[PDB]
Image (cartoon, coloured by chain):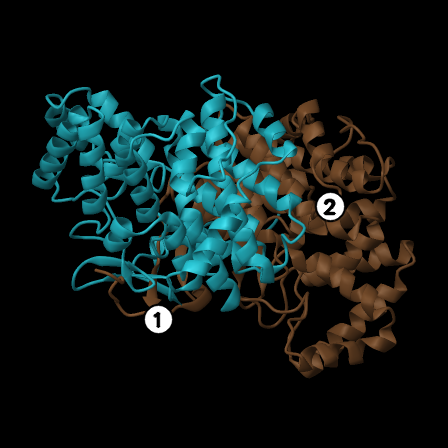
Chain colours: A cyan, B brown
């Protein structure tokens, strides 16, 4: 009996997150994500994910101090970023840069330094993503600012100014909501790489590769491309119906686990509504409502997190092609939590196949 | 019920390879690998893995000509390879190069170009591996030579001189034996990445990352480090007893599937013996023997392919740190065969977990 896509197969135990079946609450180390997103910073959530408890005041100060001192890219990195083609997909840049950073890290292959390594990657990723987004618009790097927190800083590095609080806040929430999600394809790839005792950079580079795909993190970018294509809320009804008759996958809808709605969506939809109120986003809110209602009638399939996220990022001012690297910026936390868990309770991940090829044959 | 490490779990069908059980015979598209290793070239085996059939002589001539025409790296790649730290692990150079290659490939995200992408990767990998190996010896790159076949070209690029037939033959046999091996970790990593509809370069870069670990391809490097630490066949028994008492894994022994011998080992052991007689390697042959016998007594466990490969590569003259990248050069064929099969019969790979963390708790100040 063949477990295609490992659907339904329990593959390991984890302490990092759970969907509480009763409420449909996603929890990170026991805490509901909707409450974390409403009340915490990304720094607190990252600490929580790594350590398994909320930080004390002194712990957060040390964590924040190390994060801010780790944001700078070295001269080798600026050079690589300036040199990579500016017409490759932005996920390629993130894939190459992380692999590059791994090579430079004296502790790359020392599994006992994972906490330091994960922190370094979490801190530098926004710097790389901002530079790559900006270089494609003909713009130079804006340095990390040690007076700004994680969310404010990334925004500052993208745009040159910290935007309205409503945008800072919606962005931060997105980072919290994307941070961790069990054994999704990219976290699972990271655990497969880790299962051979390979290093944390190799695992993240593998996870970034998995995340790139249209059926995983590539969806948020694809949601926005679609919304643009639709143009007007008037077109959505026909646009959808036609795509469904071609038996095509609708981006932003569909989940392996959730059957009655993604528990992250209500938080992000509200974030989208606030950003859409502040920045003239009614058009996309309308397309949202219509496309969701038509999907609920035709298929009964409810939106996943990538659906509200796509237009929210568009409205925040990000370039569409950078949506998945921005997902990377957040999911690095979940990823590295899982990598650390896998390394400390490890077994080689090595399944079996059924054969359907040529029967044994003699060399002619 | 928790399927830790997916042990014994059948996750898909493949047409690429299987082990005939009664005979413990690894086959590639139905042909025993033992036979392919004895009679074929790596070119022929790569073609077979990708196409499902051996090439006719005409098909081979053309395929080989495409392979030789795809070996070269441009200066930007050469600058990338020279810029990377000279003491990072050689697998990091391969990991980064392949990622960079993908960035440079306008067909990166087009799955209908997977065959051509696979061929380009297979052809250029040896060029990269040889440059990086030579760079650590303080030596310049040597161009790929379009008058040499796969195996001879890599040796020439490494050493400046095609060595004697015994060394060429043993190297080519190793390339054939390493090409493909079912749903091992690195192959399975490639399939998981592919399952999201990500691209062949992302998939390979993941596989490379997986192959690196000492529990997978990193074991061939680790076997040689271990043999050098042992120093002398007399020291073997004690060195081993100590490691077993500490409950450590022994590199080159253990396998998720094989229980009564690795299908590939006897071929590679004979190739090791041939190189040994022409390269003054009795010391490594004796340590091999004693270590294998000591492991059979203490644990009942037999060597895997990585055990004979290590000293074989060392006597061939390759640097220890490049052993796993040389594995990459071969295994690119199987990986990409599995990527293409995955991409053409795809389903997202997304398993479940069991939870053992904090029960639901109230965020302070709710």
Query: Disc number at residue B356?
Result: 1
| Residue A211 at least partly seen | yes
Q: Is residue A337 above or below residue B22?
A: above
Q: Residue B167 location, x and y as percent?
A: 83, 48
Q: Is residue A344 above or below residue B330?
A: below
Q: Residue B123 location, x and y as percent?
A: 65, 33
Q: Earlier in the sequence, mark 1 or mark 2?
A: 2
Q: Which residue is depicted at the point 83% across and 64% down?
A: B228
Question: Closer to the camera, A246 or B238?
Answer: B238
- Picture quarter with the C terminus of chain B: bottom left
**In this image, A207 relative to B278: left or right?**
left
Q: Which residue is depicted at the point 54% across and 68% down?
A: B22
Chain letter of mark 2 equals: B
Label 1 and label 2: CA atoms lie apart by: 49 Å
Where does label 2 land, which residue? Answer: B172
Question: Closer to the camera, B351 or A88?
Answer: A88
| Residue B13 at least partly seen | no
């Amino acid at each position: 009996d063949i477990k295609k896509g490992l659907a339904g197969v329990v593959v390991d135990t984890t302490a990092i997150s759970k969907v509480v079946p009763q409420t449909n609450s996603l929890t990170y180390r026991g805490y509901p994500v909707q409450d974390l997103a409403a009340r915490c910073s990304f720094e607190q959530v990252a600490f929580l994910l790594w350590r398994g408890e909320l930080p004390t005041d002194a712990e957060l100060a040390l964590f924040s101090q190390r994060e801010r001192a780790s944001r700078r890219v070295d001269r080798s990195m600026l050079s690589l970023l300036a040199k990579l083609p500016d017409n490759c997909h932005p996920m390629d840049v993130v894939r190459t840069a992380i692999s590059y950073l791994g090579a430079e890290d004296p502790d790359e292959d020392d599994a006992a330094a994972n906490r330091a390594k994960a922190m370094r990657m979490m801190a530098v990723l926004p710097t790389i993503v901002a530079i790559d987004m900006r270089r494609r618009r003909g713009l130079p790097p804006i340095a990390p600012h040690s007076g700004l927190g994680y969310a404010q800083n990334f925004l500052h590095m993208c745009f040159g100014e910290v935007p309205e609080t409503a945008v800072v806040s919606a962005f931060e929430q997105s980072m919290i909501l994307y941070a961790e999600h069990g054994f999704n394809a990219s976290t699972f790839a990271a655990r497969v790489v880790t299962s051979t005792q390979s290093d944390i950079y190799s695992a993240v580079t593998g996870a970034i590769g998995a995340l790139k795909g249209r059926l995983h993190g590539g969806a948020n970018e694809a949601v926005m491309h679609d919304m643009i294509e639709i143009g007007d809320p008037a077109n959505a009804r026909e646009w959808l119906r036609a795509k469904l008759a071609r038996k095509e996958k609708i981006m932003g809808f569909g989940h392996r686990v959730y059957r009655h709605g993604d528990s992250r969506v209500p938080t992000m939809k509200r974030a989208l509504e606030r950003v859409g109120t502040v920045r003239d986003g009614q058009r996309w809110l309308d397309i949202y409502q219509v496309l969701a209602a038509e999907m609920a009638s035709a298929t009964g399939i409810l939106p996943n997190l990538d659906f509200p996220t796509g237009p929210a990022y568009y409205l925040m001012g990000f370039d569409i092609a950078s949506f998945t690297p921005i997902f990377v910026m957040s999911r690095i936390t979940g990823w590295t939590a899982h990598i650390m868990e896998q390394a400390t309770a490890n077994a080689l991940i090595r399944p079996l196949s059924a054969y359907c090829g040529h029967e044994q044959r003699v060399l002619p």
